[PDB]
Amino acid sequence: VSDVPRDLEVVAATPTSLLISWDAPAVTVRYYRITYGETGGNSPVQEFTVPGSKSTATISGLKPGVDYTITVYAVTGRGDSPASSKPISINYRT
Image (cartoon, rainbow, N blue to C red; front, side, top):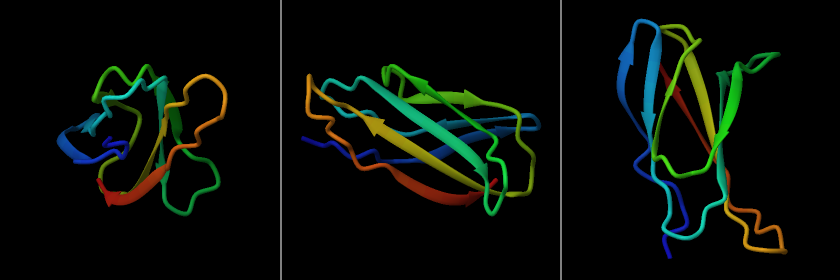
């Protein structure tokens, strides 16, 4: 029944890459969408999707010491009614 991402935390931080790790439900999750970009910007860095099969993912192309806002869109869906999940976002300085 747990259909809400959790344990969103940072495992490690390299001088040129960050490793984030959250959680994927047990239901049939089509795909996820992780977008990131500095707060108060006119052009977000970027974003990418995944079969929601992996609960972790590596990212690169950022900068140390800077307010970072990440947002994860858990898109499940079944066969018709677009079950718009509950996208959530959190601010964190990395």
